[PDB]
Length: 99
Length: 99
Ligand SMILES: NC(=O)c1ccc(S(=O)(=O)N(Cc2ccc(C(F)(F)F)cc2)[C@H]2CNC[C@@H]2NCc2cccc(O)c2)cc1
Ligand SMILES: [Cl-]
Ligand SMILES: [Cl-]
Ligand SMILES: [Cl-]
Figure 1 (cartoon, each protein chain N blue to C red):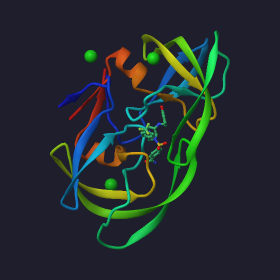
Figure 2 (tube, rainbow over the protein chains, first blue to last red):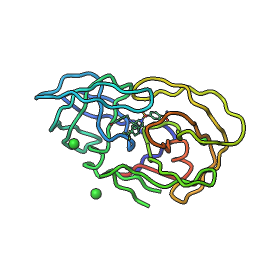
Figure 3 (tube, rainbow over the protein chains, first blue to last red):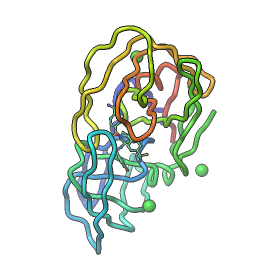
Figure 4 (cartoon, rainbow over the protein chains, first blue to last red):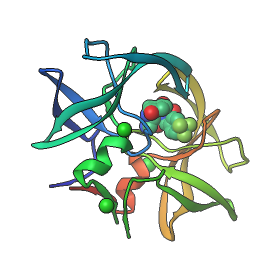
């Protein structure tokens, strides 16, 4: 599809058996999801920007379904105000910016 | 152009006659630029970032060129990790997400 930017580009995703709403975010290096359980080992990470930094848990090799497109990669879990699909997963679904 | 997301989608912008590097950020509602001198009056604006909310300066109807494309619109000035071109101006230049 082609998604315009008049409003936030929100999509439904499936992660860890749960449906969530998330923002397709080209400014995000990482994918960042609100608190939830994920399988496997994790390690702590800090990410930051406007308003400062938050601590998150980094899980690797997590499968996410985004608009019918399955992709695998690292997911950070923590107190993000909005679920974010970042570049590490946007690349996997072949998402580009066009103008 | 078509910009893939394997690296940060950084482009050159021109604002106040000066070239700067900025990030095309679909997650950002607004355009936020590092401290610089802009003309006219400003109004207060609160924006919510990954780490929390901050106040920035809002300048309206500012001329800005993004990857060679001309836009005229609202630019916020404040402490930002990088210069950010958000949805307000991405929409002006006809930028869409495609997959
Ligand atoms: N209202 C707005 O216009 C406004 C909202 C949020 C932000 S933001 O939180 O700073 N922000 C932009 C951003 C851009 C670049 C960087 C960088 F380069 F330092 F890594 C860090 C952060 C947000 C906005 N979109 C990208 C980033 N997403 C959250 C985030 C934050 C940090 C790491 C992540 O993986 C993800 C900026 C602007
Ligand atoms: Cl990854
Ligand atoms: Cl590609
Ligand atoms: Cl605007």
